[PDB]
Length: 312
Length: 312
Ligand SMILES: Cc1cccc2c1C(=O)N(c1ccc(C(=N)N)cc1)C2=O
Ligand SMILES: Cc1cccc2c1C(=O)N(c1ccc(C(=N)N)cc1)C2=O
Ligand SMILES: O=c1ccn([C@H]2C[C@H](O)[C@@H](COP(=O)(O)O)O2)c(=O)[nH]1
Ligand SMILES: O=c1ccn([C@H]2C[C@H](O)[C@@H](COP(=O)(O)O)O2)c(=O)[nH]1
Image (cartoon, rainbow over all chains, first blue to last red; front, side, top):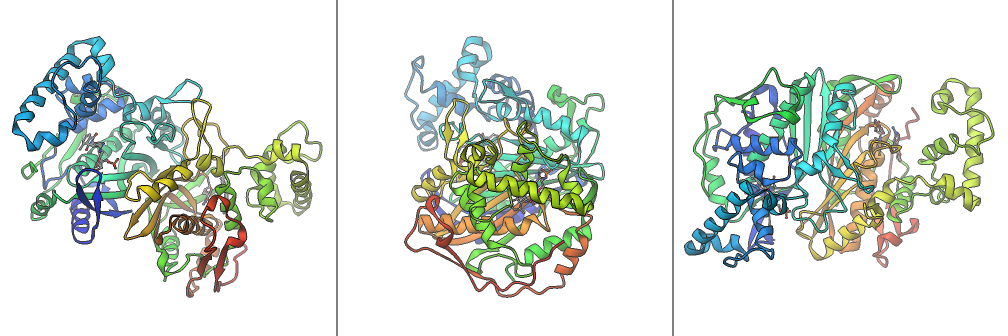
């Protein structure tokens, strides 16, 4: 079925993965250079073998598509998936007068006492980002995240460049261009920045009135990250095609390193006993074609029939 | 055999390629997202089914590895493969007082009279680049080519960054890094530059004391370009491993578009009747480990047994 390459990736890393000691107190099993392919005409590749929250994917992608890098927009859509790096910055500042949150991630699972403390300081941060404009400006803005790299790339000469916007124009006038490329990898930023982008680069291609995209992803958390990643980029492919008036082709997901953490193994093993169901179908607003101006309600997911989420 | 993925790529584009009208007066057949893999422990993947000049690959790569962008170095190694873009610039200048060379490529095959004229103006250019320092400076320098992108990336702040040099240091101290990335794709340059780089990005990976590299190549001329490309990047993988004291792993060549020109079909078809022979073996200077300082004689290719070149 449509999602089978995900399951085959997971099982390959499980049976043939190379073990490597990890930055964060674990190990990983990984393979290098694996590719998955998804024929978008066959359905939307949101995994049926584990519930994946399509709401969060949708609002995060709209966020990128706005060139937005401020978490306030995500909070306004009840999306907390970028909160941590924003919190991670405010906590390391002068203004922060509360309890110490050094290595707050590590201590959250281990001590159920500190967890409820951080739950509350992160509640304080969020509400304040939502209502305090000056605060949103200082701490809500992540600076160098996908929205800036895709839509406002900073040039040596003080200027800024909308790569994806330029590429979409190129798809419409030069569909057979071999240069329909959006990169998120800036050699000037990457030595110091918070996270050198995992979704390093993507490329479009058109044949027979159908739009394909290839993503090159240097590093992938197969269990937690990849299911979101597959969905965002497939969504992005549909959105770009919709705007250019084309049909959908393939999404080709190419990896550098793709890995499982030594502590996530039972979860993925249990997921592999599950049997893919028919894929859902995506529907887009027939009246809107500028995706830089799309809203949540312009995107509908039909007939999604997933197995339970796995909390792991 | 080792080179089989090349032959399978060629045959796939031949039997399943999508036809597209081309910028230059032809068409192409292409596929999107294809990958080849080469296990470098099994031999050096210089094609045996068609002679590929390893001398030119070697000197071009040494050129990149010096951070050099001036053609004089290539000329001094009797390598003419970058001449044309250099010529293409000098011909479009004030100083050029000779016969008109507009669309000199097109007219070279068609008129055997104009061909010998250009053969001589290009002989004039070369010798002058070799001996005239001021001229070499103005016309011999291509500016934004792989040596600059790999070793002298220009930063917004007027500075310059040795990405590959930094990455090699990272391989030695952090071999399990998921960020061993060298990009050649600069969104600021790409709208205006001569050729937006075809070898867009590469990534290293280490397991079990072996070094692998993945190349993402946005666009590939299967017949003429890819055989050189496979060899340069495999060579580069051996050179980096040698410097870091590691063994060689895989070279994984991932494509965006990979294509055949509608006029190169008979050539590739004839090549497909040929049967791969055992691969050659590469030998490197056991006394040199700084590849930024390697010379032609530091690299030896053993037991290369190729079928004839194909002039096509
Ligand atoms: C599943 C998911 C979904 C949306 C956004 C993100 C993720 C995710 O895993 N990261 C993320 C990125 C980087 C790092 C990291 N610095 N090691 C960790 C997590 C995200 O930003
Ligand atoms: C086989 C080969 C070997 C070395 C260097 C080059 C090639 C090649 O094909 N090009 C090259 C690059 C760009 C273009 C182009 N502008 N459409 C044409 C040829 C090179 O620079
Ligand atoms: O979209 C994403 C973003 C991140 N990750 C995971 C992969 C890595 O485990 C981690 C990044 O760590 P480094 O590779 O940068 O070290 O985040 C994903 O799977 N998908
Ligand atoms: O190392 C290289 C460099 C170039 N090409 C070919 C592929 C394309 O036919 C052409 C570049 O043209 P565009 O894709 O930029 O349009 O050069 C290669 O095969 N290998």
